[PDB]
Length: 120
Length: 118
Image (cartoon, rainbow over all chains, first blue to last red; front, side, top):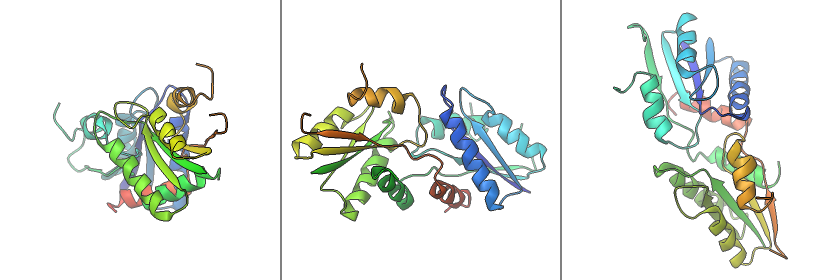
């Protein structure tokens, strides 16, 4: 009934997509959502509209979109909201989009950064 | 004798720099490094060269540069290594260029919190 759609920037290099793919597979291992999909804003497929459409086709009525971005930027305030039809510039009536917050300066990001600082 | 330099993308919007400032503030509260600085690749200051120079001028002999990026891209493979002089485009000072965040289990934890509005 509900889907998690992870959306990322995309890249002409493969690492941004590989990131989202690994993150989605880990989320799937958690067994929290019946439907998990990824979408890339630019350069690579699946795109964000394709990811949302896939979620709908699989039967999701609530689509939770999590922007896998560290900070807000034009991507998360304009481009992705536009793609999702959330701001003015096909979502069935019985489907709601829930657009969530980016990662931000989470304490766990500090933990990761310190590990990286020490090469771990 | 060692500094942590957090480098971020930078943005015409203020959120990217605000993120790096807040992260640096939280690192400083953990009292692990005598010197902590931020640098932004573009659009905004401190720049990455300025951040490294500040660290050196404060006496750091080993500069640990952590790219605050989720995944590698042209910025972490080309642009930042070039600014740091690590690839073709300081005597007693060593630059240690670390890995980005990547698909860390803790990113999954954050994503799930965000998914549920937390």
